[PDB]
Amino acid sequence: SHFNPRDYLEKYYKFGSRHSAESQILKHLLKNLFKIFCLDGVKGDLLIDIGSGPTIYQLLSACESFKEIVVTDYSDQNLQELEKWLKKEPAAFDWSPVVTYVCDLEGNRVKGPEKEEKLRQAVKQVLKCDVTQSQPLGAVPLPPADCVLSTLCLDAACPDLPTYCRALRNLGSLLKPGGFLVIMDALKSSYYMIGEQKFSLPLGREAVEAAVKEAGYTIEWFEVIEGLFSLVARKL
Amino acid sequence: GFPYRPXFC
């Protein structure tokens, strides 16, 4: 989107207007990310974030419940933009607007610099992921994880329903039996849609649930938040 | 794309 990864961040994540469609949607996603990691007791040692692109907003609550976080992406350019911020380089994107937004949502217990630092301490590995592969992280060896988080990635990463099912199973390979799978994505309606989609309103919920059951997980919680949804599942 | 990230957006 926009011209490149950075431009994309500049266009959508500066939080310049609380009423913009983008700020609205971040507010909804972060609200939910907060319930999942901070209210619903999703907790553990190691979390893998799959398809984290150049953004860190999806990890801000998560870094309170997880000793360590591994961020991954299909695109090496997203990863560089990310590292730029992680390593505190001079022309890193300013995350303060979203950071302090989350701080506020968490009850203004910490200010921005403490939340940023907490995230940096938790993130040590930055890795290529490909959801399509048997080994999502190829040759990288990782201890089994307590959580796999994938926000707005695996619906767009998988053209096929079969691939989507395969992907879930491939993601499963990273997880301790009993560990968490946290999916956020859209179920887009048929309106103004060009071409074809792998899921349907209220019915499509039941088909993504079926895909994840079939992939070797149980459904813990599914929440409607375009049809924006959460799905917490546990590996079998 | 927003809320899809590059290069999916």
Image (cartoon, coloured by chain):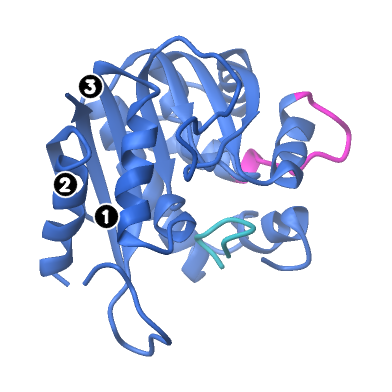
Chain colours: A blue, B cyan
**What amino acid does circle 1 point to?**
Phe
Chain-order first, disc 2 or disc 1: 2
Q: Dot 2 corresponds to which residue?
A: A222
Q: Which chain does the residue under circle 2 lie in?
A: A
Q: Is residue A13 visible?
A: yes
Q: Nearer the viewer, mark 2 or mark 3?
A: 2
Q: Residue furthest right?
A: A90
Give left or right: position of A211 versus A12.
Answer: left
Q: Which residue is drawn at 41% across and 84% down?
A: A195
Chain-order first, disc 1 or disc 3: 3
Q: Is residue A68 magenta?
A: no
**What amino acid does circle 3 point to?**
Gly
Indicate the position of residue A207 as horizontal and vertical percent values.
16, 59
Q: Which chain does the residue under circle 1 lie in?
A: A
Q: Residue at x 11, y 68 (%)?
A: A203
Residue at disc 1, secondary structure: strand
Q: Give the range drawn in magenta.
A: A87-97
State the CA–CA distance, disc 2 to disc 1. Answer: 7 Å
Q: Which of marks 1 and 3 is in front?
A: 1
Q: Residue at x 42, y 51 (%)?
A: A154
State the CA–CA distance, disc 2 to disc 3. Answer: 15 Å
How many discs mark residues in the rendered view?
3
Q: Which chain does the residue under circle 3 lie in?
A: A
**Callout 2 touching callout 1 (CB < 8 Å):** yes
Q: Dot 3 corresponds to which residue?
A: A41
To which quarter of the image does residue A214 belong? top left
Q: In which quarter of the image is the C terminus of chain A?
A: top left
Residue at disc 2, secondary structure: strand
Question: Label 3 neighbourhood size at 10 Å, few (<14), some (14-19), many (20+)?
Answer: few
